[PDB]
Image 1 (cartoon, each protein chain N blue to C red):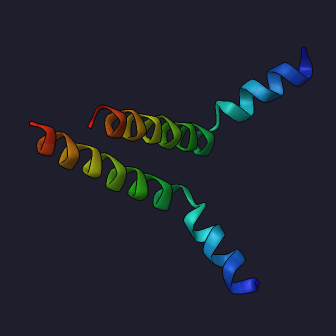
Image 2: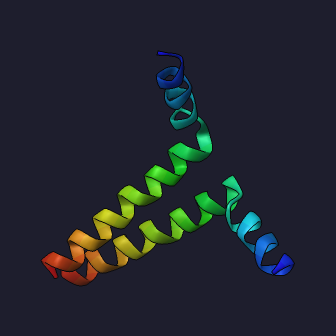
Length: 36
Length: 36
């Protein structure tokens, strides 16, 4: 439970949120290239 | 009015803006999967 809470704190940090955000928009760009 | 201003300050924080941003791009990915 402590390891899981630290992982939720690290994934809840702002830099990791922006990095996962960038991964999400890379997935959006990849799927839009698959549509195109 | 003080509760509303504190809610606008919390929603105006940078971490909550990035979290709502990630929710917006999750909605974009969901609607693009609905198009696909």
